Length: 306
Ligand SMILES: [Ca+2]
Ligand SMILES: [Ca+2]
Image (tube, rainbow, N blue to C red; front, side, top):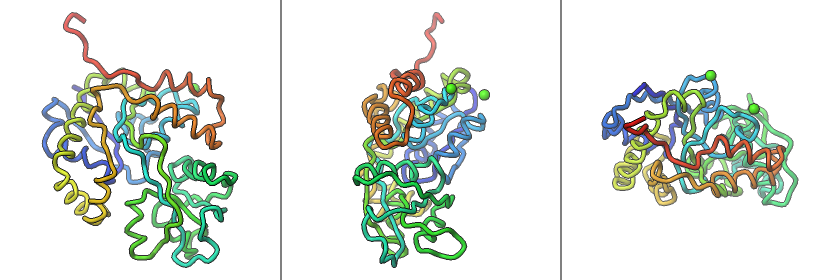
């Protein structure tokens, strides 16, 4: 089996991936996996797939679905990594008399254009009943986002930004920032994606990787105790906050055993984004693009007789 470069995001969600390596599940499947850490989200994950720097990427669902719907026929969504929805938290400065409610938002700080923090701002706007936001401050990283809403020097100011709850919880407790709203993703939060190159060149190995992840997920499920320790000792999460998170997340224990849920990964995602104004492409154009690049089956090895 050819070597496999897997791009991931160093968060609590990547826990199952770690234990799969710790317990040597990858090697057990005759695999040689080179993990590539991507601290700045799915945006770079897609770029890495486009440049063939990596074979597989584990990122947010909407990121890949939208990219495909926008005409990237070289991106393939293989399966679901996380079944439970992502909880987005809306934050603002510690002392902002001008910002107390979500409907008061005008300037929206985002890591990058097209990111989750950007896309979800539209979804939030639609649920609030207000028109989508048009003022965006590209701040690149999480810290800049916090400094921005606090109107700190060196960065452009913002009214609010959106970031994963448990990742932002630390800064609510030390009162650096202030939560004004939350919002779940209508869809499953994480998926496993690959490129057209890797899919036709390294299909058999990708399958084994998914199977290894399946075991990594089962181990996690049976060893939350160790998961809590790992997350709090290696990632920016307290043991208590890490524990709270474990009671909200549900990794796809059926990953590789059954096709992804079309309704939650594709239908809800496209219908929400389209309705929110994120996607301008027509429905049947989006459908046709997703029907070709979103798996409705599981990967399979060649039969003995070819
Ligand atoms: Ca195209
Ligand atoms: Ca290529």
